[PDB]
Amino acid sequence: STGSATTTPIDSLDDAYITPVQIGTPAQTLNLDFDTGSSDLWVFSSETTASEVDGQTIYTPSKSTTAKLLSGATWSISYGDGSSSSGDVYTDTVSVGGLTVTGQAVESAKKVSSSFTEDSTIDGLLGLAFSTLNTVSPTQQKTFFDNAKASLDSPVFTADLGYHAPGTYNFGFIDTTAYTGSITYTAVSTKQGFWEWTSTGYAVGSGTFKSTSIDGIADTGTTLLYLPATVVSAYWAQVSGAKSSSSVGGYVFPCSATLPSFTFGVGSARIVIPGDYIDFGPISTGSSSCFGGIQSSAGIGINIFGDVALKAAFVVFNGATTPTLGFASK
């Protein structure tokens, strides 16, 4: 089997991407944030504290003839941006782009933190990291990908995120028309539950490539590119007037700037992030100070190849017995 679904930026800055997901019988379609940095599929629901719902579409298990309470199961998750959610669990039929899993754990939120409430466009998350990170207790549950894997034509999914435009998540096949050149594959460590890999280095604009190992994760659920302070300083040093602002919470730059590109290494291959991808706009409405899309990972504890990096590539998440990651230009 295969599936193919379009993923759409939530706003003009590509702050995140939403993909329609069918849950239950008859189908309830929710727009979920596909997140290769976590492993819970959770939704706003009829059980979510009413004051914490503000415009989201909710899953109502009582209206689904295939929903079953997973008795005794609870979940609770805290993310790297300080947000969180928790609740109980149902199993139900879940379909993405024509690909169906029966008995998928659908984690129903009873509580969500303010940033989730405040974002009306995201109805929940669909985790695509390794199932070892799943938070359901006392019986850990599998991700949608893990459940689908054996049925897929090939045990893979691909992320093809757009810049200011829709893109595609495919399950079970590699669309050879969706990228240019060849796909370069690189090793993955699953030890921390993430799609963790090692970039072979970087360049800033038309500068020389620096060969250096940068361990990090491919995370579709993080917006920006978070790298070591040395690398980030080297980038922003090429932008007149750019500076790190503790009050704002990262590097800012004059909105009048033309940003240089940023290249990262995948083995002997190179992925080029155009400068425009690194512009996240005014820090507040009407400001001439703009927020940068490359930020320091210092204090996060891990480097994160978030959407800013991934959207410059066609990315293969290869879930074969020994997982790997593939990157191609597009």
Image (tube, helix red, strand yellow):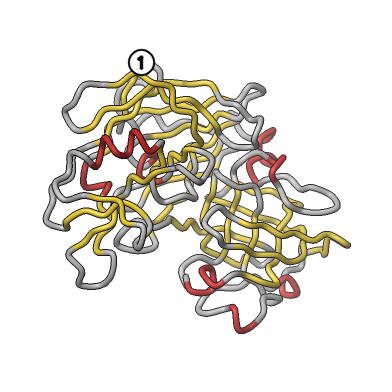
* Left or right, 268 with reference to 141: left
Q: Residue furthest top?
A: 268
From the top left corner, tell me how far across and down residue 13 is, in percent.
Answer: 31, 59
What amino acid does circle 1 point to? Ser
Q: Name the residue at 76% across, 52% down.
A: 103
**Closer to the camera in the image, 97 or 34:** 34
Q: Name the residue at 46% across, 40% down.
A: 304
As drawn, 232 above or below 257: above
**Closer to the camera in the image, 159 or 221:** 221
Question: Is the N terminus in the top left, top right, bottom left or bottom right quadrant?
Answer: top right
From the top left corner, tell me how far across and down residue 130 is, in percent.
Answer: 65, 38
Q: What residue sits right under mark 1 in the picture?
A: 268
Q: Residue furthest front?
A: 246
* Left or right, 182 with reference to 97: left
Question: Is the C terminus in the top left, top right, bottom left or bottom right quadrant?
Answer: top left
Which type of secondary structure does the marked residue at label 1 adopt? Answer: loop
Q: Residue furthest right?
A: 72
* Left or right, 318 with reference to 167: right
Q: Name the residue at 48% across, 74% down.
A: 118
Please tell me in which quadrant of the rendered image residue 133 appears: top right
